[PDB]
Image 1 (spheres, rainbow, N blue to C red):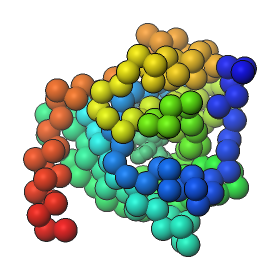
Image 2: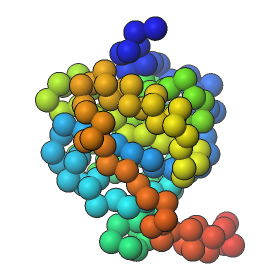
Image 3: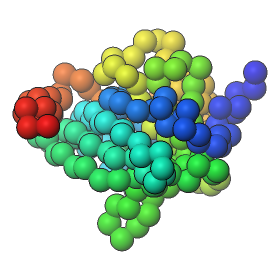
Length: 175
Ligand SMILES: CC(C)N(CC[C@](C(N)=O)(c1ccccc1)c1ccccn1)C(C)C
């Protein structure tokens, strides 16, 4: 099985939307795009919820980000472009598009940014737990290997640093 196979766009079905539904933890990312490297540098932890709306091709996103030892919560909707296998988010006068990609491990997922551009591409890595196994991490490294991004360029979260669970639990009461 060739290295790049899981870096090819895959159309998103209802089944794909079911598979991504729920809580994910941000594990790691690496990009050649400087803007993304800059934004991500400062993220210490992040977890999020996806609630797809299959009929509107949107996904409701609730996001719990830790930067500078404090909790920033945002909710918004992503749009789904099923055929291209991408999801998009409007983030300040700009639509941002990412390819939804998969690894052998069904408890992970990744998003590819600027995948058609060798000067800007990158990958972000997510798991259903804030800790990953060495198998999950190797799959991610292999994907980076395909983009010729060295492993040493990877930026990681630190689940020790999460400042957001006290907000998530406070949100659970109301909902
Ligand atoms: C700052 C933080 C929010 N970013 C993630 C952006 C991302 C992605 N490409 O993984 C996305 C961007 C644009 C369009 C879709 C998805 C996403 C994935 C899952 C959840 C939140 N957001 C960093 C790690 C780059």
